[PDB]
Image 1 (cartoon, each protein chain N blue to C red):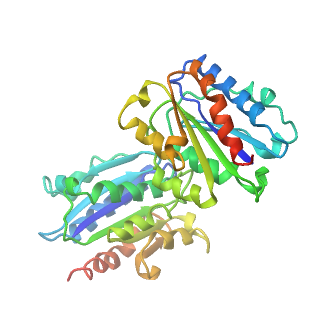
Image 2 (tube, rainbow over the protein chains, first blue to last red):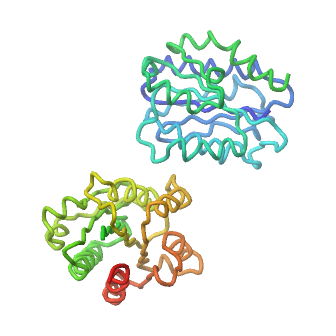
Image 3 (cartoon, each protein chain N blue to C red):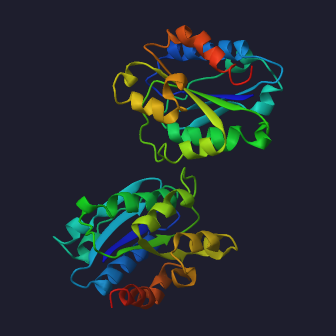
Length: 189
Length: 189
């Protein structure tokens, strides 16, 4: 599995909550680490930060090591565009991605997509195409609406009842590691 | 006929040429006037300004005056995102655009699409779906190759010969003025 994470580095995320989020990630990777499992990370906002590709991960497969030194981005939320860059670059061959592997993406967001040229209709379709399974962790009150949930149910793969985890705050991501973990194993064993 | 212009406001366009362009825009709007025409203008760079909508022109049908105040945005070149808004905002009912009307669009620019999140693949299909006939004018040494001109043809309606124009300076713009003027008459009579 070519397992990749899309992390929201919005300045709407107080230093510690971002501190937390980041501890979340190190854990699930240590936790899902088979032998042939690859990892990749990029931080997104209004700016897009590729912290590492599957291609490197294998010449230093230490989640604590690569995840520790990230620097937040503060800008706004371009989820869609980030999605496009996930498929387009991350899951590209030269970036280590292996062709006969399961393509997986776990998206962690703090709010609705704000001021992005692209839409989901623009990026989603090309994601299915290459067959990227999407799981989404949505964090915070912003996602308490009867329309916020909608965008959450959207980035996911179907069914959404199974790809959406709606948490209350950064502390609380610890609460789903087991889930998120066990779901990503069932599809390899 | 609902007719709209999209004039490149990027930074490689020196002040007096931005003035030459601006001059062109007005004269063509005059020369293409009939009691049933409407004109819309948007300049783009990295930002995007709606100078006048269709229903606002019908408030001050004075090309010349409406254009006088237009100042340069100086961004970089995001033409596809631009095509998007012309299509999503100008040829929009609420922006006074007419239902049973022809929708012509003239693109004017001295540059290759740069650092734009959208592809023409993301836009051309919408333009088509909405019956937007695209004219393209490529000013400068930017479209000096059997390559960047390929961008002109991608934007423009088929067959390409008829919808594309390229001239060396902003100062020659006057040489394709009558050739343009007529084409756009052949759409109606």
